[PDB]
Image (cartoon, rainbow over all chains, first blue to last red; front, side, top):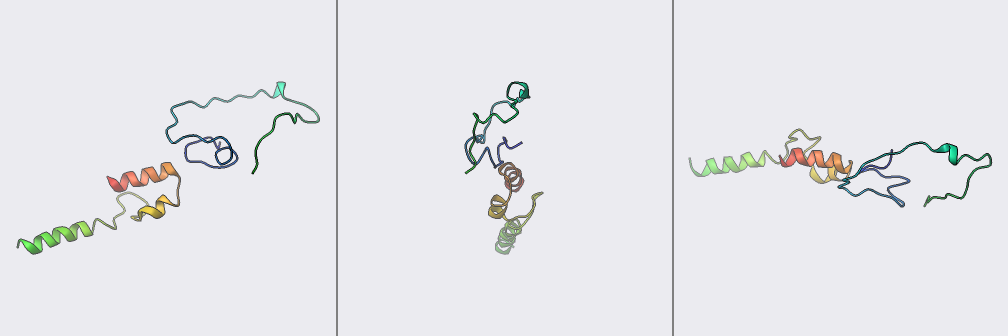
Amino acid sequence: RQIAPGQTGKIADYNYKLPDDFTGCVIAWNSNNLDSKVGGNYNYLYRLF
Amino acid sequence: DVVNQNAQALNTLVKQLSSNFGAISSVLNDILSRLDPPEAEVQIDRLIT
């Protein structure tokens, strides 16, 4: 709910922003059954600052 | 009856300065500097119209 033309945040200010003329689509779905780990899967990382 | 009339016509356009025209307020750049880009697109669309 941050990937939108005109929004900001963890996605659109740091690494991944939409252009103002996004001629695309938005599709997401859950795949937690292949990334679930008891202690946590910390191979996948992101940007905060 | 010519000249004053034209002045009144110009004064008519003077009264077109501070009209809302369906927008939030008639101030252009503050609404440009407060709201979302598509929200500002809607407001400036109303004002230009």
